[PDB]
Image (cartoon, rainbow over all chains, first blue to last red; front, side):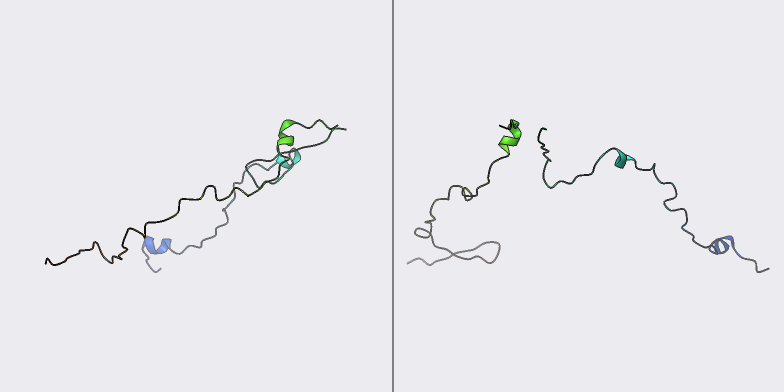
Length: 51
Length: 51
């Protein structure tokens, strides 16, 4: 039994980094209700014709 | 006749860049009355000798 200081013994560990991003957010559901459109200016003007 | 709204009718214009430089500045005529000397440091000193 090689008597070892606690500080040195603590360094004998393995980094696993498996819990990263574990707690995500609620799933996105806006794609069922909205349509994505782009823009290239201060605003976006929509126009359509009547029947 | 298609009764378009006011904003749609206002967007139906063409952009022209004939007014770009605005009004040009006055002519530069300070070389006729001033002598131009180049400085190289914090200030210039001039000295002459009396008659």
